[PDB]
């Protein structure tokens, strides 16, 4: 099941100077390395497409997800601003305590950055969060607590705690009046796009299509924002996909993927998403499960097998269905034909048990 | 769901001279090559086992299944006996003496393909009845192939009637009164995969099997393989487990009846047989330690496991519905807590070295993708 909604309203913060600041910063960090960009040429043939490339962020900073790019940059910028000096280069920042909510990857990123600086970090997770994701946050020395709240109330709690405790809210969504840090998070994500664009040029056709997954929209805004800025005159076809049960951007446009399970769009990324998305897709979980299995199990001869988690694989899963399920040849309107598609695998097996259960035992829900 | 039945009656045709004849023969054939034996050491760790090796017969002769070993050898032996000589690549003036030979069989796909392929090698005719891509692949060898409206067993009956009434040579991998010689040869021909596997383990200083897990349709393949290993490892005969689908568990059911005799039952297509082969039954009865019946999802599991090891690690390979039941069963045995007892009783632990045989690859690509990618 794919629900379609093309954008009537389709038609800077991700500019090249920010790009250079952000990349300059990440390159000085421990374990910085360009992540792989997998060319799924054999899958591209099997589906009738020009090219499929998937940016594999399961390698990013050893954290099994991309988000650290954001948290790190935002933490750096926050501290640079507290110390009044440029991103360029402890007594003055000893009492800094970061606080956030997370479904797992964001918090891990913040906890990791805090650990690098010997700063304290406090993390709240929603009811139902997997225990191993919390453990992995605690192993950076951060405090982590699985709450009895849903995601949005958990973001509320982190906010109330920053307000009542004097902690620095380090959250990857924005609402009116809490925008600077969210903006920096979005900006920090752009490194993966910069790397991907350069990896394609250094003689692969650039993207005709971008398929980008969304929780609150920060990641998608960052990535499409960048590609629009860099390909100003042939802005590629941008498809945004959410789970059926958490399709706020789809719904906004009408008016198990744990990382995407967010109800309130980020107000800083919304305009970039509204102005640039061509089609919003809502998708059943089994497409994410499919994508994980496709990524893991290319035919032995052929494309490189890799580890892509529940919120990371929804891209190939949607793409496969789009090009293979006959019920959607019409939709595939989206100009998918023998089209160069960039996807981003945003996480690896962030809960190994869930991953094995999907990829080996065939759970699709 | 695993159903258990350990064998009360547990306690030659697969001897080394036959082994040499059969291997001597297969080596002269086109595209003979030792098939890979995959060492799943990383899976072995993840499950708490000494070692897992899987013989990958998806490569065999380019046919995507092991069965050709049998059909070929049986065809050779039949022709050798018609031309009265002790067994290749023929004189065309002696083609005159074998021009009218026509092989006929029923198959769910692999057996027929093997017979059709051997017939094609000799420019002989072959006629095949099945109970769509599996049929096409049989036709491409130049054989006649017809999807019947009969079940597998009634299809075997049809092939039999046609041999009797047309003078064709029945080339079937199960047995009838007056019809044992060819079936026996089929069983014997299968042993090459076992000979290869055993040598591949020794020549890499790998421990020999403590366990064999062998899938069964009529029992010919399992009889051949366990027969060989019992003969070769006479002093430490390994623990032998035989697995069938729930819906086609005749050997299991035979063992439940406990009267020494084989008994009929009235996704794993190759294993879907109701009537045990009477030539392989005694080997099976005398040597099997436990009979297992298994749900289809274990075969599906095994296909996904085989296809998707973690990128760093074991070699990924293509294993089809009737070929992957082994690892599937094994995974469940070692991982589903409802079976730790059974596993312990079966002696599956970090001391156990398990040999499995992946009998086919993606013999229907659609079904395979649907299982491995879509679940």
Image: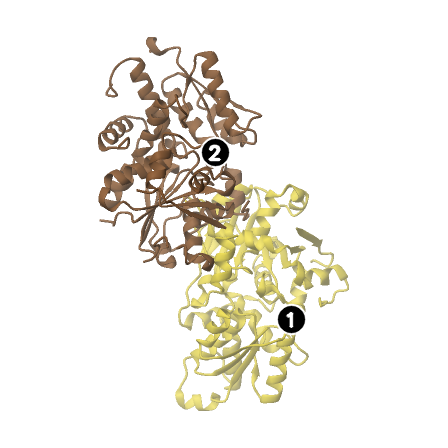
Chain colours: A brown, B yellow
Mark carried by residue A262: 2
**As rendered, which of B72 and B303 lies closer to the eye?**
B303
Q: Residue shown at 52%/86% (left/top)?
A: B82
Q: Position of residue A59 (x, y in %)?
A: 37, 36
From this view, report whether residue B86 is shown above or below residue A237. Answer: below
Chain letter, disc 1 residue: B
The relative height of residue A247 versus residue A24 in the rendered view (above or below) is: below
Q: Which mark is residue B155?
A: none
**In this orientation, does residue B17 appear?**
no
Q: Residues within 10 Å of mark 1 (few under 14, many from 20)?
A: many
Image-quadrant location for residue A61? top left
Residue B210 rendering spot, x and y as whole percentages: 58, 50
Q: Nearer the viewer, residue A273 or B207?
A: A273
- What's the residue at 36%, 29% (across, down)? A268
Asked whether, in this view, residue B166 is left or right of residue A182, the answer is right
- The Cα–Cα distance between marks 2 and 1, rounded to whole angstroms, is 64 Å
The residue under label 1 is B279
């Amino acid at each position: 099941q794919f629900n379609t909604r093309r954008k009537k309203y389709g038609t800077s913060l991700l500019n090249g100077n920010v790009g250079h600041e952000v990349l300059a910063f990440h390159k000085k960090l421990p374990n910085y390395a360009v992540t792989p960009l997998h060319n799924l040429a054999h899958l591209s043939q099997r589906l009738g497409l020009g090219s499929i490339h998937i940016k594999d962020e399961s390698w990013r900073f050893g954290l099994n997800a991309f988000k650290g790019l954001g948290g790190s940059y935002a933490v750096g910028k926050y501290l640079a601003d507290k110390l009044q000096c440029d991103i360029n280069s402890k007594e003055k920042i000893k009492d800094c305590v970061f606080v956030t909510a997370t479904d797992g990857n964001h918090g891990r990123g913040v906890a990791w950055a805090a650990e690098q600086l010997g700063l304290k970090a406090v993390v709240y997770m929603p009811k139902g969060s997997s225990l191993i994701r919390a453990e992995n946050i605690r192993h950076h020395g951060a405090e982590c607590t699985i709450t009895d709240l849903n995601y949005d109330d958990a973001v509320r709690l982190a906010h109330r705690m920053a307000q009542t405790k004097g902690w620095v809210l380090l959250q990857d969504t924005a609402w009116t009046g809490y925008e600077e840090i969210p903006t920096w998070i979005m900006q920090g994500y752009m490194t993966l796009a910069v790397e991907a664009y350069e990896q394609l040029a250094e003689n692969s056709p650039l993207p005709t299509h971008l398929i980008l997954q969304a929780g609150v929209g920060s990641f998608a805004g960052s990535v499409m924002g960048y590609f629009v800025e860099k390909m100003q005159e042939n802005i590629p076809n941008i498809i945004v996909v959410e789970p059926h049960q958490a399709n706020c951007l789809y719904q906004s446009a009408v008016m198990i993927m744990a990382g995407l399970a967010c109800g309130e769009p980020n107000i800083i990324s919304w305009p970039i998403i509204r102005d640039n998305t061509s089609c919003f897709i809502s998708a059943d979980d089994c497409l994410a499960a499919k994508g994980m299995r496709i990524s893991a199990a290319p035919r032995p001869g052929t494309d490189t097998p890799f580890i892509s988690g529940e919120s990371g694989a929804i891209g190939v899963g949607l793409l496969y269905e789009l090009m293979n399920n006959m019920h959607y040849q019409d939709l595939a309107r989206l100009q998918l034909d023998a089209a160069h598609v960039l996807l981003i695998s945003t996480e690896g097996d962030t809960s190994p048990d869930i991953y094995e259960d999907i990829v080996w035992n065939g759970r699709s829900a």
